[PDB]
Amino acid sequence: VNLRTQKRLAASVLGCGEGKVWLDPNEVSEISNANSRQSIRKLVADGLIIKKPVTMHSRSMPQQVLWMRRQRVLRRLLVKYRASGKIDKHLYHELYHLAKGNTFKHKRALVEHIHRAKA
Amino acid sequence: HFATVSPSGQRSSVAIHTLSKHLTQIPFRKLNGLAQTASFHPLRPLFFVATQRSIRCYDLQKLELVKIVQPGAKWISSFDVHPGGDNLVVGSYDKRLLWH
Amino acid sequence: KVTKKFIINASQPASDKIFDVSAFEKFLNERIKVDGRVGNLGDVIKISQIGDGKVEIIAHNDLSGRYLKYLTKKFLKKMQLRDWLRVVATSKGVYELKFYNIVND
Amino acid sequence: EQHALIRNEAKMRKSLKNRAIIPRKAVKKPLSQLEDHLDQLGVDTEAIGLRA
Amino acid sequence: PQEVSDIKKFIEICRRKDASAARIKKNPKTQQIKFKVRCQRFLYTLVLKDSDKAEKLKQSLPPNLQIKDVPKRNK
Amino acid sequence: VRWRPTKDTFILAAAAGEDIFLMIPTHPSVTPALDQASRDILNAGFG
RNA sequence: GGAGACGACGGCGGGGGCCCCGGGCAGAGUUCUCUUUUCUUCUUAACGGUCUAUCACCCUGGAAACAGUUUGUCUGGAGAUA
């Protein structure tokens, strides 16, 4: 029997592909007799039309960004120190320009330079 | 807790002071109007703040607006909550009492 | 200080005499692993039987019922019963071992 | 020999490359097959019989 | 769709001449109670949070307005 | 000028200008014990 | 008079979707041996209410021992920082 119609309607009602719809081989006569989307839903409930599971799919830095991040963290540290009063406006500006220049490489190095400046 | 209302304090107009900790906090920045008066609900942790044109009711457990009431008044002078907690009286400078 | 109660219900298979409760308990005794190693049967995970045919597990760590079901499937097909028995969660922490639907011939 | 037989059955059902298969709970199996497998393992068969 | 948190306002909305439909939603997982009224151009929902007030409200709704409980598994 | 609602103490809060004063007025209802309890309430948040 | 009414590119930031990683529930799969294991579900529209902001604008005040500040540039008595 020709079951292209049942295949298409079953895929449409089950919301899956035509490769994922399975018709019971032993019940081709009943599947052929089913020719409406209510009868095909009845068959889906009865277990003669089945949606197959999905196929197994077992699964088991630029210097621009570096400069941007280091500048942001250094400037944040200067802002924090100037807000906490460890430095004043003019020494803050001096460190701002000196850090804009590639003088400082990391937060700690900034910190020891501040110690030298203040001592 | 005791709350204070200063009309010209802008975003520091209303301030709740906890005496057991000597802490003054300002919970509600935005008030949508010049704050005039405030009061605590008699039996439920809600705070009523009356500006010139509205009274906003704020739940204090969530610090969130639960109600806005709009008396038909131009300049609200005073308000008072029922001991029950479901009725308001608003007196305004437009010579109009409003029972809410 | 949180405890866990897991129940494995093999009453029907035990009555049908297809599932050995003692053998399954032994299997879990060797294969339940605590710190990434089997045989660490301390006062962390405990195992016992009830006379009516179920296996009770008191877990103190984070033993997942998924691990219990995985070991159940392990034992079932080790005894070659995978194609004819399944494990269904019939309660919050009760896994019942029942049969697949059977067509008469 | 039994190990070889079970490996043969497994590789027979395995297929080559990731074919979606019908679940066991969806497929149905006959009383003859169940009774045969059970009494191969040594199961008294008056237990089953009404079933479905 | 509008939210209602005041029982007297819900009563007056239900007493409105165009109040068309009503239903009660009980969500037991969140132990919440909602009274929804269809009043022509909006749908209003009162949130109650308490079963004693739910019963009092159900008794106090107008008799002509047929209040009903919505069942699970809507058809 | 407003009174502290609790009957356990005798505390008066006044607002003049930009300052709020918490005060213990001398009234023939304040015992030594009531006075000390009031002062303890006021200076109980200095910790 | 406004909106309709408007070029191309560059990096930067905010937000929403997608992708990725983990835990938990349910189910499915391998399993001679090993694998607290592999895969799948875990979703929330229009519309209405409320809260949320960079730019911009306003008030006080008056800056060089110049300051503010971006990845970059620049801004400031034609009023900066705060």
Image (cartoon, coloured by chain):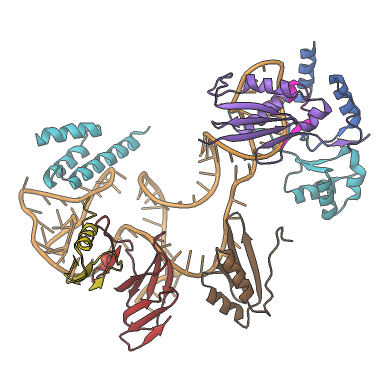
Chain colours: A cyan, B red, C purple, D blue, E brown, F yellow, G orange
| Magenta-drawn stretch contains C83 | yes
* G47 left or right of A24 in image: left
Q: Is residue F39 left or right of residue B69?
A: left
Q: Splitting the image into 4 quarters, where does residue A48 fall?
A: top right
Which range of residues does the magenta coloring cover? C76-89
Q: Is residue A71 visible?
A: yes
Q: Is residue A15 magenta?
A: no
The residue that appears at 68% across and 23% down in the rendered structure is C25
- Left of B21 or right of it: where is D9? right
Where is residue E51? Give x, y as percent.
59, 64
Q: Is residue B35 left or right of residue D16?
A: left
Q: Nearer the viewer, residue G4 or A67?
A: A67
Task: Tell me the quarter of the picture where residue D30 sits.
Answer: top right
**In the rendered image of this protein, does residue A26 appear above or below residue B8?**
above
Residue at screen point 68% across, 20% down:
C26
> Considering depth in this image, is D33 or D9 the residue closer to the camera?
D33
Residue sitting at the far bottom: B95
| Residue A73 spot, x, y in % from top left | 28, 39
